[PDB]
Length: 214
DNA sequence: GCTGGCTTCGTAAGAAGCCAGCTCGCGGTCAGCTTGCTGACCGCG
Ligand SMILES: [Zn+2]
Ligand SMILES: [Zn+2]
Image 1 (spheres, chains in turn cyan, red):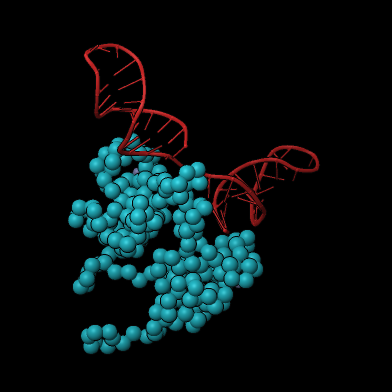
Image 2 (cartoon, chains in turn yellow, cyan):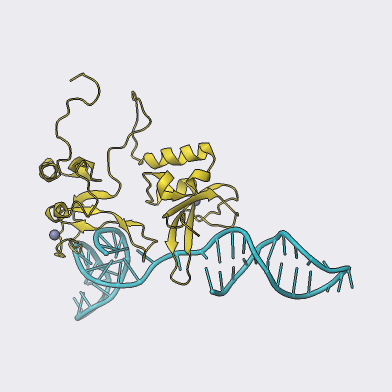
């Protein structure tokens, strides 16, 4: 297949009703909208799809920021299904709400970058290969392994200093700030300040960006 | 790559081709009956 064969996810109307959802185990009815995470098979050239009912796919941990470019078959879905996948992708769970806005939904947290206190002491900073001690603050750049596709986005941990040294190769653009790391809000104020200090991004204050109202 | 369910061909009886589906392993932190060791959730990649 020329092109259109490297995407990590696929969406389409069930070609049959024999596929079983990898999350709830129930069968996926033919013609129903289903999604799958593509995986390379070591037994033969070709990728095996792990299918899930549309809703189950998001309850396992799979995440997509831009469906049009990350999910194969997206452009061939009916318009309403293209909007449903686009909105579901934006919604990152978390019981939120709304009241006054202009565009639709809003994103303010990276899905491939996280910050948290080491849940244990067997992890290892992938920048200096030194072990991270339990309790120590660590950062990570989510990445998928072609050898372990069933895992999906796995965290690649680093010490905050080591992470900043490789910000470019890790894809941490200069416009991103520490407040965008997944898990930032759960850090003590002291820990949050240290991060904002090394990853400032644009600015810490907020004056305006289009209108004039303090 | 293999399985399997079924559509296509056949004078009929049974046979074949083919679209569609298809998967964590390991280590050990922190506990517990078993008397000196064992158990396993859950963190890691
Ligand atoms: Zn399901
Ligand atoms: Zn390090």
